[PDB]
Image (cartoon, rainbow, N blue to C red; front, top):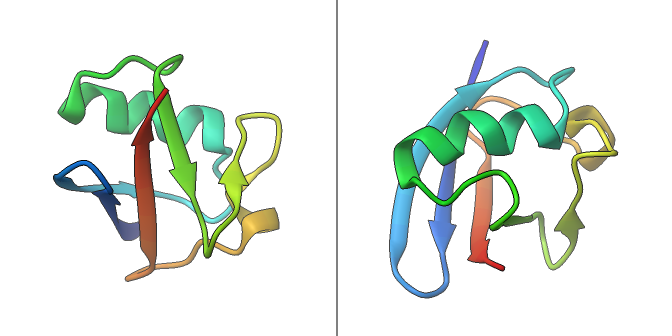
Length: 73
């Protein structure tokens, strides 16, 4: 289990835990519970890169204590 932080450009800093093998789709589902933005209106960014549910977090390289960006779309 790892702990990653998500900061929205609009103004929403929420933290959420997951796994490096966990996919972005499951990641948005767990985060959607805290932000209440639904898995269809959440957009994650990793160093100027859009994360998609079809790709796993391990592909984007998401580990414990990592920084992630949040977007509403």
